[PDB]
Length: 221
Ligand SMILES: [Cl-]
Image 1 (tube, rainbow, N blue to C red):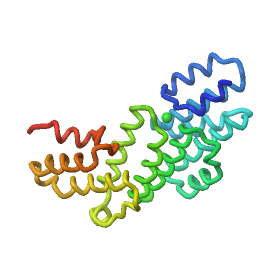
Image 2 (cartoon, helix red, strand yellow):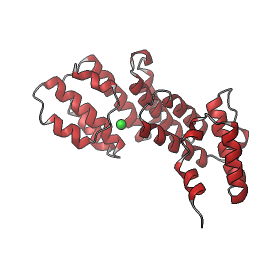
Image 3 (cartoon, protein in one colour):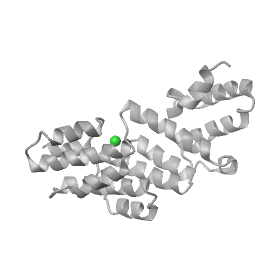
Image 4 (spheres, rainbow, N blue to C red):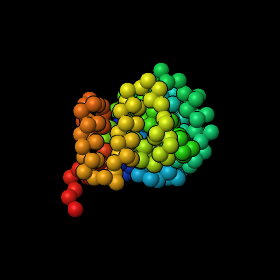
């Protein structure tokens, strides 16, 4: 059942899947390769190409329809059609989505929230996304993107945001607060980051620091 590949992470390039599309004689599997290519075209910053490829799809089975609907929502989010993106996701039953599909659902929600300049909601969505990620690079990328969202937030939001009782969110909020309070004082910043790590030793960012923080820790002027 090749269709089940849609339930998995798609790590190859769009060219990989398009080349496979040209080597497959089964119409059904051709649609699967088009859907895989359409998914990764978004990752490659080729959203219009992705949308056009979806419009070339032939008849689909139910598993393919579910995946198309998810890609549609991601395209809407990339295009800042935020209400439509949320409508498209709201029509999906999360119980029918695989972990990887769930990761993609929450990533789309995180992009919508970022589009709306709601950095806290975007971070919450990425925490939910993270629960479903097992690919090391995807997790690292999510850590870096989460940090970028926090870095972009206004200081009043960082200073007053509630963690809502969520430990992952609380660890993130205290990390960005440490950065914001001490970035003008490099000496104290390294100490502040060490103090954060010893308070949150098993937080996702403590195991795998955002690249921006690793860069600051490694670089001597
Ligand atoms: Cl992807």
